[PDB]
Image (cartoon, rainbow over all chains, first blue to last red; front, side, top):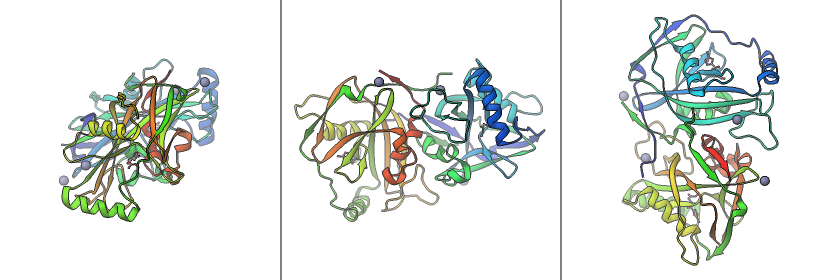
Length: 197
Length: 197
Ligand SMILES: COC(=O)CNC(=O)c1cc(C)on1
Ligand SMILES: COC(=O)CNC(=O)c1cc(C)on1
Ligand SMILES: [Zn+2]
Ligand SMILES: [Zn+2]
Ligand SMILES: [Zn+2]
Ligand SMILES: [Zn+2]
C-alpha cells in the first residue's frame, strides 16, 4: 500500500547562496543555438541533455530551485553530455561546474530517481514527453532526475544568474511563464512522499 | 545510469474485449454528486479514490485504455475506497467489479508503481497535483497507479461503456477533451522504459 518513494526536504534557510565568476552560454542567440545543434548532429548525432530537480521547503511548502538568467529565462541546472559519457556522472559533473564551491570542497550529489524524458524532433523549439509519430532521428533527448540534497550546503551561484525557490502552485499551468517542462514539475513530483525536516 | 523502471507492453490485438450488464453511477447528476460528497465528508471525512492506468501498444506506439461513458466523459477504471480499506487491495477489487469476467475466472492484477496524487480542496470540480495554500481539510484524495497487464486477457466491459485505446499524442495538452489528470498522463509515463513485446 506504501509504493511511494520517500524524500527528505529541508528548510531553505538551511542552505547558503554565495557567488562566483559569471558562466556564459555556448550560444550568443537562438539562431546560433540551432546552427550549432545542426553541426553537432551531422558529426556525432542526437544531442543528449541532463537536468536536475533540487527541492527544499519553507514552513512545510515544497519549492523547486530554478536558475534565472538575469531577468530573462528560467532553467534547471544541467547541460550537454559528451559522447560515451554516463548520464548520472554527467549531471553530477555539470552541477559541480554550475553550483560547486570557490574553495574546492566536494558537494555530495545523490541521484536515484528518473522523473521524466523529453524529445525535440526538429532543429526548432517544440519538445514532447514521447517520440512523435513518424520521427526516426530526433535531434535532442533531455533526461530529468530528482537530486536529494544534504541537510545543509553552500552553493556558489555564477554572478550572471540568481537561484530562486518557486513554489509548485506558481509553476502549475504556467507554460508561458516557464515552458512545458518546468510547468509540469508539479504533476511529475506528486508521486513522492516528502518528509518536511 | 539505468534508474528507470522497466515495463512490458503487449499488442492491443493480444486482448479480447467482451461485454456484461450495464454498471450505473452512484450519482444521477453533478449536483447529486457534490451533495453525496458533502454528506459522506461530515460522516467519515475525506473521500479516498484510486484509479488504474492500463497500457498496451500497436506497432510499438503506447496507448492508454480509457473507459468512455456512452459518447460523454472519459474515465480511468477505479473508484471510492471504503473506510480502513487498503489502496492496492481496493483498486484490485474496483477493477475486478468493472472489467472482471462473466465466467468467474480470476484476473491477475499487478500493481507496483504510484504515478501521481490529486487533491480536491472544495465541493467543486477544481483538482491540483499538490495541496493548495491555506487548505487543511481537502474533500477528496485521488491516487493513480500503473497496472502491468499479462501477455493476454479477456476483459468484460459493461454494455453502457466502451474501452478505447488513446495514443499519448492525442492526450497531450488536451485538458478540454479529457481534463487535467488524463491529459498529463504523457508527462507522468515518460520515466518508464517500455519494452514492446
Ligand atoms: C534550459 O536548461 C537547459 O537546457 C539545461 N541547463 C543548462 O544548460 C544550465 C546552464 C546553467 C548555468 O545552468 N544550467
Ligand atoms: C473519473 O473516474 C473516476 O473518478 C474513477 N473511475 C470510476 O469511478 C469508474 C467507473 C467505472 C465504470 O469505471 N471507473
Ligand atoms: Zn514553518
Ligand atoms: Zn532516445
Ligand atoms: Zn507493427
Ligand atoms: Zn491526503
